[PDB]
Image (cartoon, coloured by chain):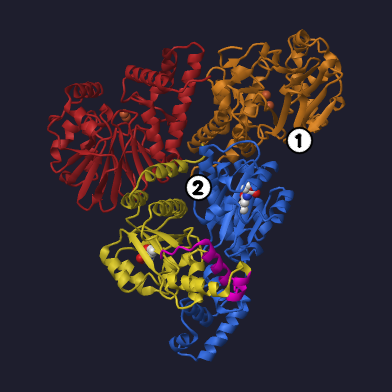
Chain colours: A blue, B yellow, C red, D orange
Amino acid sequence: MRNDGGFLLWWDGLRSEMQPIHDSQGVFAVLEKEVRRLGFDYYAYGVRHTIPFTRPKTEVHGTYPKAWLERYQMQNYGAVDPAILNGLRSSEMVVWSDSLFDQSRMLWNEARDWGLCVGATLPIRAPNNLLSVLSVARDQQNISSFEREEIRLRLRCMIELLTQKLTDLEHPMLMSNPVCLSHREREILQWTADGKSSGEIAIILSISESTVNFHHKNIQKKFDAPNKTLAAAYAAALGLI
Amino acid sequence: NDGGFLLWWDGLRSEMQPIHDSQGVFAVLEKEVRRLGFDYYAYGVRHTIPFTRPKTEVHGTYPKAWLERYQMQNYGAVDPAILNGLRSSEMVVWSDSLFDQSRMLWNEARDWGLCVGATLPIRAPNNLLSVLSVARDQQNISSFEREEIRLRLRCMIELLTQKLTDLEHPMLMSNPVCLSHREREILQWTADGKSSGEIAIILSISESTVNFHHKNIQKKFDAPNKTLAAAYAAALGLI
Amino acid sequence: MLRLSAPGQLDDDLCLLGDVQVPVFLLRLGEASWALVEGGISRDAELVWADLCRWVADPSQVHYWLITHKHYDHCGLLPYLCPRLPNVQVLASERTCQAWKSESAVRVVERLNRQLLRAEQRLPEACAWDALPVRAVADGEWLELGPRHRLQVIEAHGHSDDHVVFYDVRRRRLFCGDALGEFDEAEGVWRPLVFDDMEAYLESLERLQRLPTLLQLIPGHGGLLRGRLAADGAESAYTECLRLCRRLLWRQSMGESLDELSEELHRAWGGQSVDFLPGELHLGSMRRMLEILSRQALPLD
Amino acid sequence: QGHMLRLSAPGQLDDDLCLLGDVQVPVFLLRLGEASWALVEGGISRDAELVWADLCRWVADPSQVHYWLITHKHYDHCGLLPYLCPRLPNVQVLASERTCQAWKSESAVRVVERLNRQLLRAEQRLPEACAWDALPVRAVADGEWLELGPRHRLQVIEAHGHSDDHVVFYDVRRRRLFCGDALGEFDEAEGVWRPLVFDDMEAYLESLERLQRLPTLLQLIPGHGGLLRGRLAADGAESAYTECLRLCRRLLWRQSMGESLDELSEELHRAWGGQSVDFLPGELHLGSMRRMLEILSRQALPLD
Ligand SMILES: CCCC(=O)N[C@H]1CCOC1=O
Ligand SMILES: CCCC(=O)N[C@H]1CCOC1=O
Ligand SMILES: [Fe+3]
Ligand SMILES: [Fe+3]
Ligand SMILES: [Fe+3]
Ligand SMILES: [Fe+3]
C-alpha cells in the first residue's frame, strides 16, 4: 505494498500484503494500519446474524476502548445500533450524525463520551445473508465530503477483502453455526420449505415416508430444532437451501 | 489528491442521480461498459424462492435470440456465473474450467460471440442476488485491466442496484406481503420453534387467537402450513 | 525505451506520417479501409504523400479524416491532400467546421503555414475551404471506424474553444493533441498550453482522468508515450497547470509583471517548438496563457 | 500584521510570536506568559551573539526562557544550544529521542561542530560552550502534548524522511505548524517547495501525507524563510508532496535517457544552491543533492 502512485497501486499492494497471512490477528493488524493511514483513531468490525429472529446475534471486534465494549455488550446496544441497522435497508455508507442517532440517544451520548465523536459505518451482506459492517471513528475532525467519498471507496475495498480472508480462515465470529446437510437432506429440506408434506416428498424422491421422516429427524437434530418449522426457517435464513 | 478513480466515481454518481427512469440508468451502464472496451453487458436478479425453481430475471444487451434460447432452456437455473454469487463475492473471469459442468450453455454462448467476459455478484439488502456481466468477442482479459475492471464493476453494480431499488423496478420487486408488528412477532416466535401455546403464553393472549393469526399468515402466503410461511419469511428478510 | 518518436508504424495498426513535430496519423481499419487523424501543415505535404506511399498501396481507401481543432499546426493540409481521397468524410466539431467556413480564420492559418516553407519548396495544388467533405460530430459520438477500431470523441475545450480528443477503447489509446500541453522532452513533464479558457482546460483534463488507465498517449507533438507517462498524463498535466498558476500568482504578489514570466518562459521553453512556431508567436502565446491564468486563477489570503 | 503572504523580517510576527536572528536561519520566540517564554529551532552557531541581542530586546530576564523546541539533529538546527543554554538556566531542550541521543554520539556532534565552525566571519570569536551530553534535555515522543503555556499547547508529530529523527510541532490553537525541513526549502523566487529528502522517501511522503490531514493551517513556519500564511500555508503539505513526486518523475525520465545522478545533481545545484550560500557550503549542498537523487532513484516507483 500500500503506497502512493494511484489507487490501483494501493489496491494491489493491499492484496499482496494480505495474501500470505495465515493468522486472523495479522489480518486485523493490517486493517488497523490502513485505517490509521486513512486518518481515524479507532475502527470496528461487526457481524449481525439473522437468527434468533427475536434476539439476533450481533458480534463485534475492533479497537474501540474496551470499557466501551463492556458497556456496549452489557446493555446490548448492538441490537438497535443505527449504524448497523442501516445495512439491512441500504448498501450506502453511513456517516455518523446527530440526526442518524435521534432514535438511540443514549448510545450516541455514551459513544461521544468515549471519544467516538466523529465516524462512519459501511455495511455489506456476505453471500450467506450475514450483515457485516466496518466502522471507523476519530475524536476531533468532522468528515468533509471529498474525504467522505475517499473513505467510502477504501473502506469498501477493505471490508470486502477482510470478509473474504476471514471466511477463508473460518473465524469463530463469522462461523455462526457450522451445519452441513447431505445432498438428500438438503433437497428434502428444499421440498419441505416449499410446503410439501412427508408423503409428497416420499412420492417425489421415490423413497418411503419413513425414510423421509427419519431424514427430518436427523435434520432437526443438526439444527437443535424441536420441529421442521425452525429447521426450514433457519436454513432459509442461512442460505443452505 | 487521492486517485484519479474518484473522478470517475463522482462523475458516475452525478450522472445517475438525476435520472428518474430505469431506461436512462441502463443506458448509462451501457455507456460505461462500452467505454471500458466491452461489447455487451447484462444484469441479472436471482430470487431465493421457489427453492427448487428459483426465479432468475435478466435485463441487458445480449442478442434477443440468445435470451430466447436462455429462457427456453432455463439456463438461469444452472448458470455457473450466477451460481458463483451464492458462495462467493469475488469476480469470475469466464473460462472453460468454469463451464465444465454446464458445457452446452458455454458452447452456445461462444457460438454467439460471447467468447470473453466476466461476471461480478453482489447481495442486495433484501436477500436478493444481483449480478453484473460484461462480454466481448476477441480480446482476453489482461491482468491490470482485470483488477481495474473488477473495481469499476463493483462500484457500478452497487450504484445500479441502489438506483433501481430507489426507482422501484419490477425485476427487483418481490412477492408483496405486509405483516403488522403483532403478527410479525408471532412469526418471529414460531420460526424460533415456539408452539401455539408457548406463543400464547409469552404474548399474554389466547391459543385460539394465536392459531387464528397463523391462519391469517398462511392465507397471505398462499401456504399449506406454517413451515412454508416461516421459510419464505426468513428468506425475504421480513423477520 | 519509454518514448516512441519516429515516422512510420507505431504498433500493429497505426502509422505516423510526416514530421513528428506536426504529425499525421494513419489507422488501418481493415484490409481495404484507412483513416487519418490531424490535419498538419502545408510545409509537410511533400513529406506526407511520399512517406505515406511506403505504407498504403492505394490512396483511394481513406474514408475518414479527424481534426482535433482549428490551429494551423493541426489542419493546414485540407488544400493539399483532401482532393485526392474522394471517398473521405472529414469529421469535426461544429466549432472546427464553422471556423473553416470563416475567411479570417483560414487567412490566419494560411499565413502561419506560409511562414514555415523552405526557400526551395514549391506549393502543390490546393482547393477551397467551404467545399470540404465535412460532417459534424458530437461529444461522446461513437465512430465505428473499423472492426477493431471503435473510437469515441470527447470534447476537450480549454486549449481552444473547440479542441476534441479521441479514445480507442480496445487499445486504451488516447489521441489528445494539445489539451494536455507540450511534452518536455528533456525533463519529462507537461507544459500547459492554455490559449482560450483555463477552467475548460482543467475540466477537460478532469473528464479525461475519468477514462480507463491509458496504455498509449498520443499528443500533437513528440510522438507516443507508454507506461506511467500515459497513465497519469492528465493528472500530471493538471498538476503542472496549477503549478504554473501558483508561480504566476506568487510572482505577481511580489510586484512582477506578466512580461517578466513570459520572457522567462520563452527563454526556457521556446527552443522546443522552434521548427514549427515563430519565436515571437511563442512569446505571445506564453503571454496569452499567463493573462488567462492571472484572470481565472484562485487568489490567496 | 500585514496583507503579505510571507513574513520574512526579524521582529514580531504575531501577537505571541517573534523571529530572531537571520531570517535565513531564524529562531522563533513564543511568549507563554508574562514571565515565561519558549524558543523554537536551534539555528546555526555563528548567530549566537546576534540572536542573544535580539532576544534581550523582548525578554527582560533570560531565566524566564523555560523551553526550547528543536526539530531535528542537522547542524543547522541545533548549533546554538551549547553556546546559549549556559545563559538560559531555566531552559529545557525538547527533541526526539533520536535527536537527543544524537547529541550523545561523539561522531554526530563532531560533524555538527565542524560544519558550524566552517561558517564564521573571518575573525569571529566563538563564546564558551558546554558539552552536548550536558544540555538540559527532555526527550519527547510522537503525539505528546507539550503544556508550554496556558494558551500554548503544542503537539509533537513524527516527520521522518528528511532525516531519521525529524519531528514537527503543531500549535493547534492557532493552527500553526513549525515544520522545519519536513516540507523542504521554500523557493523564495518561485513560490514552490524544494524537496529535501536525505534519509527515506517513503517516510518523507508518508509524513507529508499525515500532515495533509491536519486542520487547515493558518501559519506554516519552516526552518528557513520565515512564516507563510493564508493559502500558501494551507496547502503546504500537498504542495510539498507534489513537488517531491515531480522531482521523482524528472529523475526517472532523465535516467530513462541514460543520465547519471551527478548530472542532475549539478543541474539542481546550479538552480537552487544560491539560496543557502550563507549557511551551507556549496560542496555539502551538491552532496545533499546527490544523496536525495540516490534515495529517489532507489525508492521511486519505476515506469513500466
Ligand atoms: C458494528 C459497528 C457499530 C458502531 O460502529 N457503533 C458506533 C456508533 C456510535 O458508537 C458506536 O459504538
Ligand atoms: C446473469 C448473467 C449471467 C451471464 O451473463 N452469463 C454468461 C456466461 C456466458 O453466457 C452467459 O450468458
Ligand atoms: Fe493547438
Ligand atoms: Fe499543436
Ligand atoms: Fe535539516
Ligand atoms: Fe535545514
Q: Give the magenta range.
A: B175-201
Quarter of the image where one finds residue B173: bottom left
**Which residue is the site of mark 2?**
A8
Three-letter amino acid code at the position of disc 1: Ala
Identify the residue at horizontal 56%, vertical 49% (top origin): A155
Asked whether residue D10 is drawn in magenta, I would say no
Quarter of the image where one finds residue A20: bottom right
Q: How much space separates mark 2 and mark 1, taking CA atoms?
A: 34 Å
**Which residue is the site of mark 1?**
D141
- Expressed as whole percent of the image width and height from the top left, the position of residue C210 reads 41, 42
Image quarter where the N terminus of chain D lies is top right
Depth order, front residue of B104/D242: B104
Crowding at mark 1 (Cα within 10 Å: few <14, some 14-19, many 20+): some
What secondary structure is found at the residue carrying circle 2?
helix
Q: Is residue C256 visible?
A: yes
As drawn, A144 above or below B145:
above
Identify the residue at horizontal 77%, vertical 14% (top origin): D48
As drawn, B38 above or below A108:
below
Three-letter amino acid code at the position of disc 2: Leu
Depth order, front residue of C55/B216: B216
Ligand 5 quadrant in view: top right
Depth order, front residue of A226/D282: A226
